[PDB]
Image (cartoon, coloured by chain):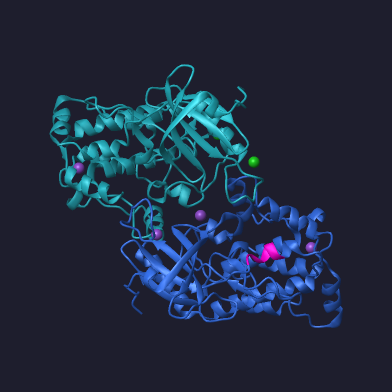
Chain colours: A cyan, B blue
């Protein structure tokens, strides 16, 4: 149960540019002095007691670390080390510096559904790895879908940010309200038992956006968004979906399901004919279906 | 009605940060023309419905609309509103005496009669809002401020109308918001909201004021939400050994899941802990004390 390292992080690491942050965490590029190899340092601020406004609980820090220690897959971020000082716990993580998937897609000259599906398959492969280990990510959304390097022809996806991830336990009910409203399943909004299915919903949301530039449930305010989610009110309006294949629409429709039991599981998603064509006729349809990147760019730029 | 389009810094000298909440920063200011001091709340405007940051126009207009309606001695008073390309700026009454709980934490001695003095001020403020069908929706200690620490019994101002909402008869309002420690079950459970949620939050505030302890606060949000939704709390003698039965009964009527059964603001004002009916009740309340040591220990942890 490797103890967290008590030595000063700056004594063993050079610290460079900010990569990002959340509410109680900041991420910075770093380099281990002894090896010269680069990583990302995630500084998580510790709480004072339990009614502290600021900082993350020990339970929550330790859960994130436990889960990260378990994971070794080519589509998931890998943990290098953990340090702790008076104010923070510092996670030294694989450096993933190629930006968000969506930023890369926004710069393309064109995108086919075949190309789209080989990005989505990479996400599905990392999620399958997690789900096989009974790990739910619980924060699947475009900003946590990162690329190693944006300058190879077909960039490699890494799932990041395990701050909400949780191990699903046999016969135990897990209920909580968390995440970004746009991307959360109805069981989160409704304070109902949660499990691996919630990740599958989020995958339908990400796929919908990827293909269209629009978001299925997003309203003018949070109040509207929550109402849309819980009533599963979304469309495939021709404004945004004119170019989309029927199999793409079927894939999404099978993920954006309220009843957790009826939603595709990760292995069912992987086998779905949009991802895994059954014949050449279908492979052709998928190759010839394009994404309107204009709409995609328009909406991605607006999120910035 | 229109927001002022002139540059706020042309009419105000702008000073130190006093607070920096959600997508809002509050700074001290003085209006050049009059010499009078105020607080300037700068609210970042959202750029798109899924902009990562900023606040929707709907939400800004709602806070302003509500602020424009409220004029009461226990409620912050709006002075003016300015808008630029970036922000909408609310010029508010400057409330400089700090948080109520910080004042209470310095005291040597606090009786329940004194505590009810402060609670009644909150109830008066809330009564004024509720009569206008305005739910505050963010009642918690950090929004209960003082004008001036240096009078015998300081004057309370309810601040921070960022979550406030007008409650319309027959129109269902459902949403999930607020600070978990302080939110009512109907918030957690995504059920119809109204004026009752504020009453729950008053019970929580009261519980904390009297004990230093928080009724539903768990080790993590997951535990807090389960505590709230099951209405799981206690009056542990560790924290409540000094507390009167009157005070416990007031709390017990507010920390109720069933919205219809929860005390209303008028019922809270008439409760005998607040408004004794006889001298026997008055003496019990006067003689019951708060253990300020526990209060202090717990308030300093929030620091
Ligand atoms: Cl802790
Ligand atoms: Cl876990
Ligand atoms: Na499409
Ligand atoms: Na907003
Ligand atoms: Na619910
Ligand atoms: Na007490």
> Which picture quadrant has residue A72?
top left
Position of residue B255 measured from the top left corner of the image (x, y, whole percent): 66, 63
- Name of the residue lying farthest toward the top: A35
Quadrant, the N terminus of chain A: top right
Please indicate whether residue A240 sits to the left or right of residue A170 in the image.
Answer: left
State whether residue B98 is above or below residue A277: below
Please indicate whether residue B110 sits to the left or right of residue A121 in the image.
Answer: right
Please indicate whether residue B257 sits to the left or right of residue B15 in the image.
Answer: right
Q: Nearer the viewer, residue A260 or A183?
A: A183
Q: Chief secondary structure of the magenta span?
A: helix
Q: Nearer the viewer, residue B43 or B191?
A: B43
Position of residue B125 measured from the top left corner of the image (x, y, whole percent): 60, 77
Q: Nearer the viewer, residue B288 or A6?
A: A6
Does the rendering let one see residue A38?
Answer: yes
State whether residue B153 is above or below residue B21: below
Give, as a single range, the part of the protein colored magenta. B98-103
Does the rendering let one see residue A171?
Answer: no
Quadrant for ligand 2?
top right
Position of residue B152 measured from the top left corner of the image (x, y, whole percent): 74, 76
Position of residue B251 measured from the top left corner of the image (x, y, whole percent): 71, 66
């Amino acid at each position: 149960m490797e103890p967290f390292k008590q030595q000063k992080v700056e004594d063993f690491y050079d610290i460079g540019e900010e990569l990002g942050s959340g509410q109680f965490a900041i991420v910075k590029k770093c380099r281990e002095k002894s090896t010269g190899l680069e990583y990302a340092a995630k500084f998580i601020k510790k709480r004072q007691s339990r009614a502290s406004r600021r900082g993350v609980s020990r339970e929550e820090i330790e859960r994130e670390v436990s889960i990260l220690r378990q994971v070794l897959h080519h589509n998931v971020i890998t943990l290098h080390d953990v340090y702790e000082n008076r104010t923070d716990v510092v996670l030294i993580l694989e450096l993933v510096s190629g930006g968000e998937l969506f930023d890369f897609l926004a710069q393309k000259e064109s995108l086919s559904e075949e190309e789209a599906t080989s990005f989505i398959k990479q996400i599905l492969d990392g999620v399958n790895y997690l789900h096989t280990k009974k790990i739910a990510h619980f924060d699947l959304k475009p900003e946590n879908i990162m690329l190693l390097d944006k300058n190879i022809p077909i960039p490699h996806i890494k799932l990041i940010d395990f701050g909400l991830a949780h191990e699903i336990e046999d016969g135990v009910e897990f209920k909580n309200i968390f995440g970004t409203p746009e991307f959360v399943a109805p069981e989160i909004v409704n304070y109902e038992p949660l499990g691996l299915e919630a990740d599958m919903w989020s995958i339908g949301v990400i796929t919908y956006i990827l293909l269209s530039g629009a978001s299925p449930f997003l309203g003018d305010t949070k109040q509207e968004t929550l109402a849309n989610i819980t009533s599963v009110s979304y469309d495939f309006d021709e404004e945004f979906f004119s170019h989309t294949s029927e199999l793409a629409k079927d894939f999404i429709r099978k993920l954006l399901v309220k009843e957790t039991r009826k939603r595709l599981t990760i292995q069912e998603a992987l086998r779905h004919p949009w991802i895994t064509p059954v014949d050449n006729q279908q492979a052709m349809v998928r190759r010839e279906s394009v994404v309107n990147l204009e709409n995609f760019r328009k909406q991605y730029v607006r999120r910035r």
